[PDB]
Image (tube, rainbow, N blue to C red; front, side, top):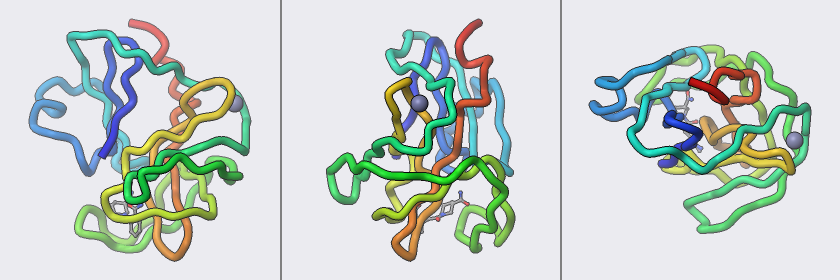
Length: 140
Ligand SMILES: NC(=O)c1ccccc1CC(=O)N1CCC[C@H](C(N)=O)C1
Ligand SMILES: [Zn+2]
């Protein structure tokens, strides 16, 4: 589990959104595994606006932050899970690193701010849902 709190927005994995998230919905995209809801209190995270391919991510199954090199946001094939059938996920970035069912939501960050959140994994890989193209998260 895990979320990004920027301004009056909460960014979570679509597959982990609560009833309260859906009842206060701003935007969602199944093909990116993203959902954004509105909040009463202001958040303290800042979103990166860059093309960094290195950063650090939080892994809850190891209680540790790991440095990683990661691919550019792309259309990648993802195996079936209890949450989605086997399909292509868009705006996804891969890196070599530990991931487990329960690690989705962990933040990926570079020198400029929050890059994205854990969304896929397995086989010694970890996948991140990119949020750097979502410019509207910086206002309203
Ligand atoms: N990091 C993990 O969640 C993980 C790690 C090892 C093995 C498997 C996973 C889980 C995973 O890949 N999922 C299940 C949740 C929905 C995901 C999606 N965005 O389509 C696919
Ligand atoms: Zn950066």
